[PDB]
Image (tube, coloured by chain):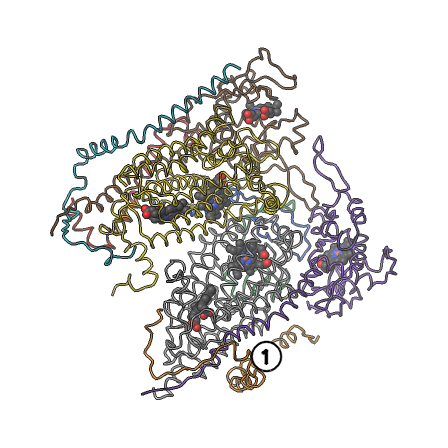
Chain colours: A green, B blue, C cyan, D yellow, E red, F brown, H purple, I orange
């Protein structure tokens, strides 16, 4: 968290440079992150699965 | 007989019945400060909020 | 104990051998197998069976002795 | 020239399974080698998958095998295959031994010695595998046979405290027995290769006892498809046992968690140890009873050194054949008396059957052999 | 029938193996239907499909 | 008194080699256990996920799993509060410790009901005769801390016979006699002893058909290959 | 005449060990095969003791290893012996491989192929054994290499969800790895017997590469006492590492409970993978990286099919020998660069090191064999 | 962030044959029992590991019997605390690890069994970490993290305990900072390796055996190879 | 391989002596140390130049690593 070039995500296993939403622009990382089946409720909660 | 043997032994190495039980969690949001990540257990893997 | 070529020295023998496709799958099964198994059964009745009837008689004797001991008390 | 006669592994294959001059006189009582081998590799596979889901600890073994039979897919039938395949392996092992005693093939001396050592190893592997499910029966039988090993004066106490890892059957004993049952069938397979080596030194045996070197048919493809026939017969019998009546062999008390206080009253080993156990409890001597068992296996060593006949087999000696069938009935008698509770007429007939066992195999065999000998103008 | 069958499917090894694999899949399908039909047929009633068919 | 009474083999619906189990009776028996017998007997190796496609439905499995709350883990403080649980739930222990049940009785721990059919000499018919055969002692009572039951090694039990004319009078028609609840609990204990019964019978049918297929074929091929040596003949030439 | 020449065991022992015709001009480089055998039986013995004191359960694995190291008498020396003996096993392994490529014994093709299969089996054995202590580094290295297995397009997903033992690494993963870490070394032993059997079929090789049928001395007792010399030096090294520097090769992050959420930035495995992980993290291609690894060991397979020189030694081909030393330095460079974290000059020189690896092997050594073939008027 | 490599110190046990002072082990255990056994645990060392190493019989029994146990069942079966004779571990001041994270300002304090062996450096790292509390040169300091450059990230949620509460050793050593820090780091080195004295004993054994035995087998190999090293060839044709 | 059907060698006389009667280490300090000095003369031209290149790459990569780790920019 708060690492890499773009300030967002940064894997230390091979130095994949992600953005804040985890999108690769430097490294051999093939794909980007997957949105889970989550839905917010405005009581500052979220159902995740 | 041989392909049924292969099917039953692959099914024995396939999975376990209790592993297929996985949950739908409820997560609270704003206990995490502005600019911080935190993981929650889903399937053992980290769950980035 | 070894491979072929050196095992025995036999003259005076001619073996006839028939093709497998030449003859039937089951050459006279019922007309031969039943008297042959009757002969092999009669060849072992008084040698195989009298141990087992001794087994069953000692079985029933010891069993009824146990029952008689456990039904008077 | 020929690829089979050039490649060095294929030379071993050719000398093992193709150019083996076999006796043409052998019926289904000689299929037992392939039967025991296929039983061994299926035991390897079933125990391997069990070990992929088994936990060797006293707390976790019962629950983990429960998790296997209820949760892991087909683990219930794989466990049933392992246990009932051990039972089928025992049936084939006893009948292999019975063939080797009946048809006079026990004149092969060092092959018989290798078989005796294999019998030791299969007994040890069987007992420790039976210890592994952490049952009440397994706990108490392990305690009893551990004290049987403590019967040895001045060496046995240190040896039993050496194999414990504690005061009794605790987690150290459980994991050590797991290691030995987990490693031993490879050594069994190696000594089986040695067994096969000495037999292919000598050459196989026919029912007559006369060497069939004038009538050698090859090992392939005749005996290969005949062993396939016998093997699939074993498959159907074994699989119908594991899928129709799983409970005709397994003890009911084997499905209980181990209580370190109970000692349930019908405590017994499994049926392939009860004839080993009926000799014990029908002799009022601890060291005497375990020495009687060890001497029974040593009698099985001795019997190649008392063949004072002039034939090879008992095929044409009917008196010794009838004594052999009385010994068969006496073996099943000792097994059933091992399968009974300790009762006074059962005590009497068990002692009489054990002393009858010793008197038939030890004394009556050279007596019957010498009556058969001197009867035939010899 | 027999002469036709031997003259077609018993002189090349690979075609023989391929047609017995294809017939093995077809026989596997037919045996699935037959065995499932028989085992559901001799134990009608107390089977979960009808109790789920309630609901 | 060292004279056990062996249970006869009874005409069940799971009697024969082609026979099966009543999942509706399994449903009735689990309602019996959960509504009567779970308070005194542990069945810890059975979960609600074993009750999905056997007799029950999906959403009612969530209903049953929310009927029993056990525990959640640490809420960053280890508070160990009460959680419903959706599908991963197991069945709760009535007693946290064995001596909790020992002090709740005269010792005499109620065993776990996972394996009891396959765990005593005599299976489900032993269970049926055990729950059925209650009568009075003619002359022999021992200390009046236990009860009377002939179907027992030792002939005395600390368990009261929990049947007594409709303990539940449950959901469908099915009048709650001794016999109906005993048949349902025997079917349910048989299923608890084997989770894979009718699947085993289906594979047994498959295997009987396949061994009726192979045994003409393989014996025909063995007879065919050995047919050469069955046909050979000898002749003497000097 | 002789018990050694008539008894069937001692026939094989005599024609393999005593009267084996071996060449005579051999330095310490041919001790390494016997040292691999001694390390094989020694590591099997230490693993046997460990399995008599280990539990494969993720809740209790780390505490069980701690129980071995502290509570069990000498379990610390046996654990250190198993670990450092595996390390010296890899040392003797790469020395044996370097010898077989350097003196040019790779012309024996099936021996080379059996050696490659042994290399695969030993690497998988050692990796699953390194997973088995159930530490932080074991957990995360198993995670990364499991996903490397999942890198296969269209085929890898079912296979790696099948070998997960779950949705991720859990108790089932640990038990499957324990089963394979047990079962592979005996397969390695049997294939080592087949390796030595093909070598005794061919006959051994001198340092000169000249065929040496005319200087046959027996293996007994000369090379037996030479192997005793090598064995005593190798036991010296092993005892030195277990008595003074346990913590030298032992990685630090294998000493904590495996936190499933920590992921320390230290990511490198034990040193016998770092040559290959550097090949992985150089090429910016997922399938290309795993393909480059598999192609690296397959180039090690197809090393003899690029041989075209007219003498099999490197002692008389000097510039090819210099290229061999450059290849040794390249391998050690790849290992140390795999023993580093990832930054920009490291990325540059790791990519360049992989490029120099395959450039030196796939091009320069056959072209050097061509030019020193060409120089001698050939 | 940067990462400072710690120096190497001339420890009196740094030499490859020099042991540990058991007196230093006793006083370092006194350090651990006074102030260090309140946030960290050392859950893999029992009191019987101290009775032949740093105390006598009754001393270690008193140290093991002044501690609670919360042992298991009684006649009712619930719980009861206990002194505990010798099988006691250290009584885990933070029971749940997430409750440990909620105890302080996050970053739960780890156990101290393998810390000398597994923190990228030996006891020098621990000593410099304990004494490295110093002045921040205009850095972040997010309200719960303390500045220490002997740490990756220089932000530690552990207060400096080392000058505060001089603990009154039973021998009576006047507690400075570095003396008590050296003693507790030596105790942690022992807690890493209890085998240290015995492994240096067997190192002495093996070094004498390989200093006297290695030329013997080498000379024996040259003795048996003395033939082929001395053979000479000659060429006779006809 | 067998032992007796390997080659055909004529014209050969071999002298050798009993291993007891000659000493154990004949001039180990008079012949073996110039022998290994001859080996050292005959090896370093083929063995040595890779390792010095590796040592230079080692030190260069380490120093570039630290100088890339520490920046000290201008602002
Ligand atoms: C509380 C009172 C109950 C209730 C409601 C039930 N059981 Fe029974 N049970 C209880 C005790 C205290 C004991 C111990 C005495 C003993 O084991 O002899 C038992 C015993 C059993 C047994 C064991 C018999 C045997 O293994 O031979 C079984 C199988 C058993 N109980 C079953 C059972 C069932 C199916 C119940 C629901 C109808 C049931 N018990 C109710 C205490 C209690
Ligand atoms: C409660 C307050 C204590 C006490 C009495 C001691 N420690 Fe320390 N410690 C503590 C926390 C909350 C942390 C973690 C903070 C962080 O993650 O930055 C630590 C950490 C350590 C470490 C590791 C270094 C680190 O992780 O930053 C060591 C080593 C250490 N603590 C040693 C130590 C010793 C020897 C103590 C006895 C004097 C001791 N701690 C007391 C909280 C607390
Ligand atoms: C451990 C299990 C055993 C295995 C796997 C095994 C394996 C074999 C095999 C493969 C053969 C050759 C084929 C055959 O005739 O069966 C064989 C033959 C034989 N075995 Fe065993 N055997 C075992 C146990 C024993 C024992 C305990 C003995 C008795 C000491 C024994 C004695 C013999 C004899 C005498 C033969 C030759 C019989 C003949 O020539 O017909 N075997 N065994
Ligand atoms: C090396 C291969 C083998 C392994 C890894 C192995 C492993 C195991 C394991 C883990 C168990 C306990 C689980 C269970 O009981 O179902 C077990 C039980 C058992 N094994 Fe093995 N086994 C092997 C070979 C054998 C062999 C060759 C036999 C004898 C034929 C055998 C006989 C048994 C028996 C009788 C039990 C007890 C069965 C039971 O009570 O459920 N095993 N084995
Ligand atoms: C798995 C571990 C291995 C074992 C236990 C092993 C065992 C042996 C043994 C005992 C020898 C004879 C003595 C010697 O020359 O040192 C030998 C020689 C040999 N091995 Fe291996 N080996 C192994 C791995 C390999 C590998 C990976 C290769 C390469 C493919 C290989 C290729 C050779 C060659 C070419 C020889 C003959 C060398 C010569 O004649 O100079 N071995 N091995
Ligand atoms: C079948 C025999 C073997 C058994 C039963 C066995 C058993 C074990 C066990 C239980 C462990 C975990 C405990 C520990 O880490 O010290 C282990 C670890 C290990 N084994 Fe084995 N092993 C065997 C063979 C081998 C072989 C042949 C090698 C390779 C030379 C090997 C290399 C390793 C390594 C590298 C570790 C990790 C050491 C560590 O991280 O502490 N094992 N083995």
Quadrant of the frame with the N terminus of chain B: top left
Residue F189 visible in the snapshot: yes
Q: Quadrant of ligand 5?
A: bottom left
Taking D338 as reference, is A3 above or below it?
below
Taking E30 as reference, is A3 above or below it?
below
- Residue at image mark 1: I55
Q: Where does residue I28 sit, x and y in percent of width and height? A: 57, 82
Secondary element at image label 1: helix
Q: Which chain is disc 1 placed on?
A: I
Q: Where does residue C26 sit, x and y in percent of width and height? A: 18, 39
Q: Residues within 10 Å of mark 1 (few under 14, many from 20)?
A: few
Q: Where does residue H233 sit, x and y in percent of width and height? A: 42, 84
Taking D209 as reference, is A28 above or below it?
below
Nearer to us in this view, D244 or H230: H230
Q: Quadrant of residue H20?
A: bottom right
Nearer to us in this view, I58 or F115: F115
Residue D37 visible in the snapshot: no
For image coordinates 16% across by 51% down, the residue present is E7
Nearer to us in this view, I72 or D251: D251
Residue at the far left: name it. F237
Nearer to us in this view, D9 or D309: D309
């Amino acid at each position: 968290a708060n690492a890499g070039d773009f300030g967002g995500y940064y894997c230390p296993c091979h130095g994949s440079h992600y953005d804040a939403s985890g999108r690769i622009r430097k490294g051999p990382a093939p794909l980007n992150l997957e949105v889970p089946s989550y839905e917010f409720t405005s009581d500052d909660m979220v159902i995740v699965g | 007989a041989a392909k049924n043997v292969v099917s039953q032994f692959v099914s024995s190495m396939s999975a376990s019945a209790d592993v297929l039980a996985m949950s739908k969690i409820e997560i609270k949001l704003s206990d995490i400060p502005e600019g911080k990540n935190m993981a929650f257990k889903w399937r053992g893997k980290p769950l980035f909020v | 104990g070894r491979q072929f070529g050196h095992l025995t020295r036999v003259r005076h023998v001619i073996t006839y051998s028939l093709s497998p496709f030449e003859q039937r799958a089951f050459p006279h099964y019922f007309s031969k197998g039943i008297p042959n198994v009757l002969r092999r059964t009669r060849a072992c009745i008084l040698r195989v069976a009298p141990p087992f009837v001794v087994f069953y008689l000692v079985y029933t004797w010891g069993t009824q002795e146990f029952e008689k001991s456990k039904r008077k008390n | 020239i020929n690829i089979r006669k050039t490649h060095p592994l294929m030379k071993i294959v050719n000398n093992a399974f193709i150019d083996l001059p076999a006796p043409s006189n052998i019926s289904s009582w000689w299929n037992f080698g392939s039967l025991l081998g296929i039983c061994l590799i299926l035991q390897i596979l079933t125990g391997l998958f069990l070990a992929m889901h088994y936990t060797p600890d006293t707390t976790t073994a019962f629950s983990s095998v429960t998790h296997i039979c209820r949760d892991v897919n087909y683990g219930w039938i794989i466990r049933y295959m392992h246990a009932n395949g051990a039972s089928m392996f025992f049936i084939c092992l006893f009948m292999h031994v019975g063939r080797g005693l009946y048809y006079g093939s026990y004149t092969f001396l060092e092959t018989w010695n290798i078989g005796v050592i294999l019998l030791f190893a299969t007994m040890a592997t069987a007992f420790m595998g039976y210890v592994l499910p952490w049952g009440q029966m397994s706990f108490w039988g392990a305690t009893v046979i551990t004290n049987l090993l403590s019967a040895i004066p001045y060496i046995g106490t240190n040896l039993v405290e050496w194999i414990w890892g504690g005061f009794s059957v605790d987690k150290a004993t459980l994991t050590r027995f797991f290691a030995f049952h987990f490693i031993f069938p490879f050594i069994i397979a190696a000594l089986a290769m040695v067994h096969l080596l000495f037999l292919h030194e000598t050459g196989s045996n026919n029912p007559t006892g006369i060497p069939s070197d004038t009538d050698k048919i090859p090992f392939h493809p005749y005996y290969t498809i005949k062993d396939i026939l016998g093997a699939i017969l074993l498959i159907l019998i074994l699989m119908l046992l594991v899928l129709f009546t799983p409970d005709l062999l397994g003890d009911p008390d084997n499905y209980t968690p181990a209580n370190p206080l109970n000692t349930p009253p019908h405590i017994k080993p499994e049926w392939y140890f009860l004839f080993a156990y009926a000799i014990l409890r029908s002799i009022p001597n601890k060291l005497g009873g375990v020495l009687a068992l060890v001497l029974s296996i040593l009698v099985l060593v001795i019997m190649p050194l008392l063949h004072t006949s002039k034939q090879r087999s008992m095929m044409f000696r009917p008196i010794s054949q009838c004594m052999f069938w009385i010994l068969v009935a006496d073996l099943l008698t000792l097994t059933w008396i091992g399968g009974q509770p300790v009762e006074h007429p059962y005590i009497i007939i068990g002692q009489l059957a054990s002393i009858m066992y010793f008197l038939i195999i030890l004394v009556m065999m050279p007596v019957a052999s010498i009556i058969e000998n001197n009867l035939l103008k010899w | 029938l027999t002469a036709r069958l031997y003259s077609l499917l018993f002189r090349r090894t690979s075609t023989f193996a391929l047609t017995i694999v294809v017939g093995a899949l077809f026989f596997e399908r037919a045996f699935d239907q037959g065995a499932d039909a028989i085992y559901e047929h001799i134990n009608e009633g107390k089977l979960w499909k009808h109790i789920k068919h309630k609901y | 008194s060292d004279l056990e009474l062996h249970p006869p083999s009874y005409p069940w619906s799971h009697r024969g080699l082609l026979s099966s189990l009543d999942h509706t009776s399994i449903r009735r028996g689990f309602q019996v256990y959960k509504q009567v017998c779970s308070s005194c007997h542990s069945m810890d190796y059975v979960a609600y996920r074993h009750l999905v496609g056997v007799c029950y439905t999906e959403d009612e499995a969530k209903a049953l799993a929310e009927e029993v709350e056990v525990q959640d883990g640490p809420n960053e403080d280890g508070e160990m509060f009460m959680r419903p649980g959706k599908l991963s739930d197991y069945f709760p222990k009535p007693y946290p410790n064995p001596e909790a049940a020992r002090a709740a009785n005269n010792g005499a721990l109620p065993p776990d009901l996972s394996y009891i059919v396959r765990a005593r000499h005599g299976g489900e018919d032993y269970v049926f005769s055990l729950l059925t055969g209650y009568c009075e002692p003619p002359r022999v009572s021992l200390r009046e801390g236990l009860y009377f039951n002939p179907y027992f090694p030792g002939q005395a039990i600390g368990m009261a016979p929990p049947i007594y004319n409709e303990v539940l009078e449950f959901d469908d028609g099915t009048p709650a006699t001794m016999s109906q609840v005993a048949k349902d609990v025997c079917t349910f204990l048989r299923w608890a002893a084997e989770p894979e019964h009718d699947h085993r019978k289906r594979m047994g049918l498959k295997m009987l058909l396949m061994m009726g297929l192979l045994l003409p074929l393989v014996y025909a091929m063995k007879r065919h290959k050995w047919s050469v040596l069955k046909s050979r003949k000898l002749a003497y030439r000097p």
